[PDB]
Length: 213
Length: 216
Picture 1 (cartoon, each protein chain N blue to C red):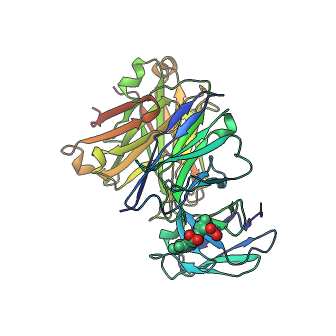
Picture 2 (picture 1 turned 90 degrees about the vertical axis):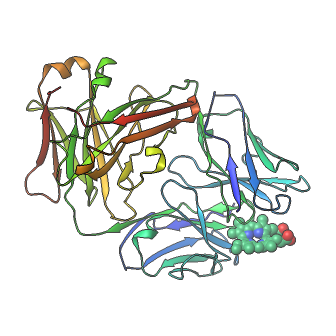
Picture 3 (picture 1 turned 180 degrees about the vertical axis):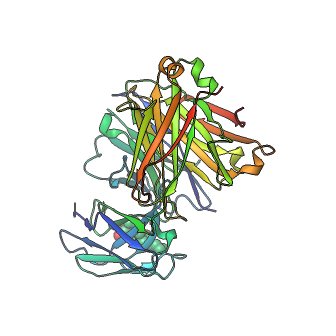
């Protein structure tokens, strides 16, 4: 079963910094170790096999080293294009084993979010539900507080949010918040407000609307 | 070019059994062995088993040994893995890769639920000519109330791909998944260029095309 323990679980370097990932075996394997890179979405890509050889195409900035029971992969000049999850594998003894994986984010200057709001489509209203969407575009870090305030009143439990994986080119994130209420209450109140408190602003910035048409 | 096209996302009822495909080409199939890997939402990676296309011999991970079975078809160049007595733990994304895992498939998403499929509705997030400024405008599509994952969404038939952000799916209380896809574009084009989002939900054989026009 050879348990491949991978460390760390979540690393985070800056563009140009170097990344180091270690994978320890529970018993000596030898040289049959490998590493794969999985970018969010698509499946894994082979990066290094036989502990240190690079698969054709893989840039020289990726280095596989170590041997015996401790293996390590290094990224010399971390570039936004390396943002992804990485995996360690062992193929000397069955069953083939993988490491727990490491997620690699990127540090960068802050970015306040560009906030937008979208009233519910006339379409959805008919179905008897009114979904209101607030969007926070390209910001960093991801720690962002989105508070929904319908007519000077705060909501809670009646809204969900999703955050994108780190942009493979901006190193930023993006968040959407959807206030889901009944076609009933939506026709009642008039002021729909979205307030966001990011660690990049002085006071809570806010976008809002009023049932127009 | 080496390609490993596979089954589309399939929903399967608890206890039933599914048989996944993996059609190979671009290389002499009977030479390299075939693998199968289970991923499963946000977790690691588990090797399932190996199968030799030529002979027919196989080697399984003495874990899925009982639940899965690998077979092939010398002619059509297709590998088959069959899962039986499926449970919630069995829900995951399955990949078939070539011997040295240099080539993988896009993977098939297998969701095990007693619930039944439901095609998503699609509502437009209208470009707010007043609440979407700064020289550039944001617009999008809300993909709501569908099950199970996944749903793929591209814009203007794939012709538009820059500034596109498709958010991860969210499971609502209703037990249905919701999701949205936005895109930033030059404000000046809102009056000339047409934006259409194409939403695809294989599990229910659904395809929707929605035009997003500036709300007035």
